[PDB]
Image 1 (tube, helix red, strand yellow):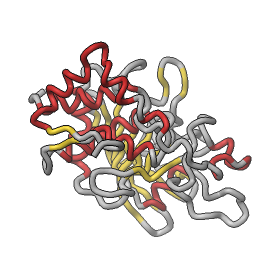
Image 2 (spheres, one colour):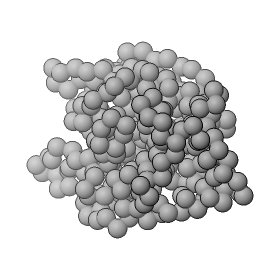
Image 3 (cartoon, rainbow, N blue to C red):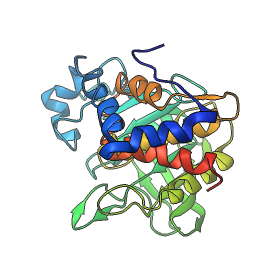
Image 4 (tube, rainbow, N blue to C red):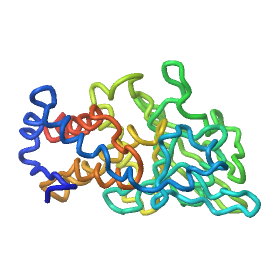
Length: 287
């Protein structure tokens, strides 16, 4: 098709890349520029209520109404159903990911409740808590093995595995007499400015994640700072790598356009838009 899908025939992806990157990413920069309006017209009524105003890390990153995850309502709290997060499509399901902002201390309770209510068995954290001096995301998980209660959810570290660019963490999650495990994928290498360089690091992580998570059927929670740029770059990359195993086509454009329609600025910057292409380019060319 043509309008919300620019599919490439894999056997030519390496040329398409050249052709796209050529002239200071002329074509690339231009292809991206088409998405700059996708889904922005959609209402954000709830996110925009007074009682939910303090819950948003950024005033111009708010979940569209049709896509937002909703927390079980609480009978005295007005607007208690709210959290900054949308179901965003993945390779295997329309409601495969829940991408959200990095919780504030003011929202980590809500954030945990979402994981529990969503039945999500995997969080993917793509930002550092602090970076270059700002705070991006509140430490919403214990930093030792003493179990910590976030609301009604008791989170405890069963073990963690540090690597070069990310740390795996296995949480036990308890609500009442009910127990589950959750795997926490924390990519800790992303550069203070720009996209990961070399991008291979990100591919490496996505492989580690997917290999580890399998053909998951409940939601995966994905987050960064605002829940748009990196979150969008990961999900897309995860999708396409799964994809090149069942098709001789890839639709990075198509993937983004679909995500935009679901949650704001999903692949945020054309550097990330390019980065996705480089990662795949790297894979198709045997690193």
